[PDB]
Image: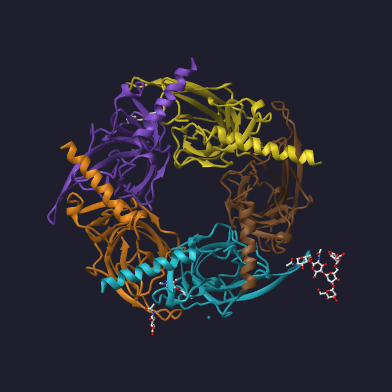
Chain colours: A yellow, B brown, C cyan, D orange, E purple
Amino acid sequence: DYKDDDDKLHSQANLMRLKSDLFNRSYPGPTKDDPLTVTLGFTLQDIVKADSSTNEVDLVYYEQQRWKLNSLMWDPNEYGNITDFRTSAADIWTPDITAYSSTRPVQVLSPQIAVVTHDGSVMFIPAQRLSFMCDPTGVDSEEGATCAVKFGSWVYSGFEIDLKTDTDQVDLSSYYASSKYEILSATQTRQVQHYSCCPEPYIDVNLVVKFRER
Amino acid sequence: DDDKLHSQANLMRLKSDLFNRSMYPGPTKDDPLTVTLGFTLQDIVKADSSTNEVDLVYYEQQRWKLNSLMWDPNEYGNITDFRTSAADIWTPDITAYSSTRPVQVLSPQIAVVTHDGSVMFIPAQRLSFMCDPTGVDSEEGATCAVKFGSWVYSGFEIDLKTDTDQVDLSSYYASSKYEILSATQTRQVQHYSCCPEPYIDVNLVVKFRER
Amino acid sequence: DDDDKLHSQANLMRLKSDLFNYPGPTKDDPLTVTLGFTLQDIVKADSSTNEVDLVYYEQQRWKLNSLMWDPNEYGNITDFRTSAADIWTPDITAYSSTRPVQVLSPQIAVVTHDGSVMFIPAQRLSFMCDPTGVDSEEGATCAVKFGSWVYSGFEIDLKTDTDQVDLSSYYASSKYEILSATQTRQVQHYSCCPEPYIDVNLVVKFRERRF
Amino acid sequence: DDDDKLHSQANLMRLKSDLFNRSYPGPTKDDPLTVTLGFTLQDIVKADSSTNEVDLVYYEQQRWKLNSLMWDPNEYGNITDFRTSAADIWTPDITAYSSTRPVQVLSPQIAVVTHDGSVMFIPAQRLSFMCDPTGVDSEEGATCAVKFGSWVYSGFEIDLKTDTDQVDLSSYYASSKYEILSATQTRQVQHYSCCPEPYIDVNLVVKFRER
Amino acid sequence: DDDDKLHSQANLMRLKSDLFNYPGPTKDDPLTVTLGFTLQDIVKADSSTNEVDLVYYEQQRWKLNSLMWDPNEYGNITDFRTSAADIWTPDITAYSSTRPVQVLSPQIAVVTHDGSVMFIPAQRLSFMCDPTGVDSEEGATCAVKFGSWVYSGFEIDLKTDTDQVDLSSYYASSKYEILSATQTRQVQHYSCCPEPYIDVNLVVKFRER
Ligand SMILES: *[C@@H]1O[C@H](CO)[C@@H](O[C@@H]2O[C@H](CO)[C@@H](O[C@@H]3O[C@H](CO[C@H]4O[C@H](CO)[C@@H](O)[C@H](O)[C@@H]4O)[C@@H](O)[C@H](O[C@H]4O[C@H](CO)[C@@H](O)[C@H](O)[C@@H]4O)[C@@H]3O)[C@H](O)[C@H]2NC(C)=O)[C@H](O)[C@H]1NC(C)=O
Ligand SMILES: COC(=O)[C@H]1[C@@H](OC(=O)c2ccccc2)C[C@@H]2CC[C@H]1N2C
Ligand SMILES: COC(=O)[C@H]1[C@@H](OC(=O)c2ccccc2)C[C@@H]2CC[C@H]1N2C
Ligand SMILES: *[C@@H]1O[C@H](CO)[C@@H](O)[C@H](O)[C@H]1NC(C)=O
């Protein structure tokens, strides 16, 4: 009725005001004094192509990214019980998580939209097709081939951005059942590197996939 | 000539009243939206048995209705609908769940808005998706499927529906390398252990064989 | 002498400011778009996917009262070149493409004082075409319709000046020779709806260049 | 000395602001422009006899002069030239008339502007164009040609010139799959049956053979 | 507690505001760009077109007086990360590419309080290279020069810290093994023209593994 109509109008107004209060009335990225931990997890959907002439393999996966900022916190009571909202990834800071051994620019398969929750947590899940350095020799064997690719910030050291995983098991529950390649194992493991150049520690998540022709 | 100038004026006024004035932030649990989807399959262009990818060309009809897009035609020279850039309005984030390449858009990004607040948007797309074409060279043919739905909105914010579960095949290319044996489009509701919300998709299932 | 050149520059800048400082056609204010093709090359015929690649220049012409001016009010300027982004342009689309059109020319149009616009995009188009018989005397025949994506014949009409495609610039050393090429206005109806839909059907008969 | 360097930056920022922010609508019949063109051919990368397309890599030197880009160096700390993004200034729409794919740009889009109003802009490009490479595997080689000129400006608005009819081969890749027998670049006044006003082009003719 | 973090953010926002409120190098205000390559992979060698595809990280470093600050004035901030669109970057270009470079990393740079900027684009490059001999003990040798497209040595000098390409990240299971890889500053002089031209010549000797 008129009341219900008003409730929907109010909710829209509350959401606009919240987004206004948060964005254009107020993030420069993490710092050594304010470091950020980004949680990463992979959902491997398909090994599309294994190219033995170039040693490039093409994966399709969803990369779940999570982080939390005090600057994105709000009290739902102050905004009509809004507890989360969807917003363009361009409206907010997002981490520069990059494959370290790609051979072509990553191709994005999903909308650039994130979910922000009232505790300041952000969830962003880009689907990607990636070509990366991988020798598929042995893919036509019982033990298959094994390849790996590291993901992490391009420009922030372990001083500013840390990474974590919730599990070292890649999510395979959406893996394409009729892929040319069957997955024997898939793991995701945080690593901390020290290079002789630099005093800063460097952090990545290493995606290791063991696979064979089905 | 002055009559047409007035019609031009009424349309510019309508669009400015609706857009450059008035703030729809997308759907929410308190203001949920139903998007109607329908496919018109034009061609299976390519089936790649080395990678198990198949390439489709189709028109994806999308329809939804917003109170914020309603007007009284009597206040605007009896204008009952208009065409506008899809960039001028909210559009749903309907995504193929098992694509293997970014969708390629084949048509202009323009929508039709009607006075009741309904919007119709029909992007033509070329899609590569995960599909094993084994059997395509047999009488039984091959069967593949791809789900479409919102990437970021659950069934609490966006629901989906179809007007028919039969894919429109009236524009299917008569001399395609592949003949269609059947094509269906079916709403599915899924509940996951992770999550209390329902998740909705439209499953496009195509059975086809070499012609 | 160069004083005159400064004055002509200022007049043109003032004209463009006055014109640019249109919501598309409507049933009350319909527009006729004239189309014509200049076929330059059949680049590729792919029998594995039934796609053929053409390179052509597509002539588009239309006329808007809103683009009219009196040359005497603007230092006798009769026409100007401008970015296609500065003006409304018709959403003329191939109906059976299989890849996005690739644009081969600058997106710049010519506007004349009577409000007429001429815009000539060069394009490479892949479209649905079975090239069977291309290696024979009779050759292969394919066709592709072009028209508005979103406007009916009650908002945009189409016309051609001739039903003969211009072949005078067709590449003399193409892999494919043209047997004929026509461009024909068609009026289509769909069962749901009383309004006519208009397209221009490009039909090309061709064979491999070699009794 | 660091004071001097700060002054130089200030002077350049002020010059650019004066030229771009506080001050050209392209050439016209009253104010026509001459563009000088010159090609430096770097490589014939690929010759495709299946589609009759050949791929070139070259640098295209473009030079023109505008009164609107003139300054007195004395008013700007003796600055005689500057580099600037090609987006900041008008640039000519020089286009290959027989490309089969959009040209791919290989160099930064930055031009050099000199105090007399002259501009030099040298885009490196990879171009696929219409070319039958028959004879490439013989002593006499293959011959192909491609015209470059304005897409939309007739010879009444844009004229072209060359400094030499000899293509610069001094940077030609010495281990290319193809050796160059000759390469010429020749101004032409080109009449099209579509159009009463001629267009000016520079015709690049390359004779080449497998190494 | 969190007031400390609220302060550091405010300090960084203040710094970025003060710095971003430069027209490129000139003969009067010249710049030095240091370049270094980390060669990751020879992906493809195409003997039908004489094009070879490299993947590498290209380190670029320069310093601007205009980007200097005292850390003590901004809560001891000594560096920050910023979009490469926020700042001037050098027009370093391969001189014999055959396709546009494809960028594999985010366009973000690090600015340090001494005015130095480090920008490290990862790239895939196709360039002119004849792979003949790659299947022999001696392998094949190719080369590609990198340098500014529009600035002479009077505006941008180039240099390398070492003439040895960094091979410590070279892909161990590449189709091609690297025999040597050098990056060498070259100065070119022409009779027409007073100005020196500078490039860094990347020379790679490689063979089938
Ligand atoms: C925008 O669109 C609206 C809606 O269609 C138009 O408004 C209509 O205008 C027509 C034409 O003037 C009207 O038709 C006339 O209706 C009369 C009776 O009207 C009463 O009854 C109707 C229905 O119950 C009510 O809607 C209305 O409010 C009235 O109470 C007839 O007597 C008229 O017939 C006579 O005139 C015609 C010529 O016009 C002759 O040919 C006949 O022989 C006869 O002498 C006539 O049919 C209609 O009532 C209006 N509809 C509504 C809903 O208001 C606008 O005209 C249109 N344009 C603009 C600019 O707004
Ligand atoms: C800004 O670029 C980097 O820091 C990269 C890289 O940096 C370099 O390779 C490099 C090269 C020359 C000088 C300094 C750093 C190290 C690790 C691996 C990828 C990424 N990274 C965090
Ligand atoms: C505006 O487009 C043109 O003038 C093109 C072309 O125009 C046409 O082909 C054409 C066809 C029909 C009507 C008007 C122009 C003429 C020459 C060749 C390419 C380009 N041009 C300089
Ligand atoms: C345009 O030309 C006509 C020719 O008589 C002339 O009368 C008129 O003054 C000119 N218009 C101006 C604005 O230069």
Q: Find residue D56 and report its image quarter.
A: bottom left
Q: Find residue B7 and report its image quarter.
A: bottom right
The image shows residue C154 at horizontal and vertical percentages of 69, 70
**Residue found 41% across the figure and 30% down from its top:** E13
User: In this view of the protein, which residue sits in the foreground, C50 or C159?
Assistant: C159
User: In this view of the protein, which residue sits in the foreground, A122 or E140?
Assistant: A122
Query: Is residue C162 visible in the rendered structure shown here?
Result: yes
Left or right side of A106 for E149:
left
**Residue found 31% across the figure and 46% down from its top:** E93
Left or right side of E127 for A180:
right
The image shows residue C78 at horizontal and vertical percentages of 43, 76
- Where is the N terminus of chain C found, in terms of image quarters? bottom left
Query: Which image quadrant shows ligand 3?
Result: bottom left
**Residue found 81% across the figure and 41% down from its top:** A1
Q: Is residue D118 above or below residue B199?
A: below
Q: Is residue B120 above or below residue C140?
A: above
Left or right side of E27 for A32:
right
Query: Is residue C176 visible in the rendered structure shown here?
Result: no
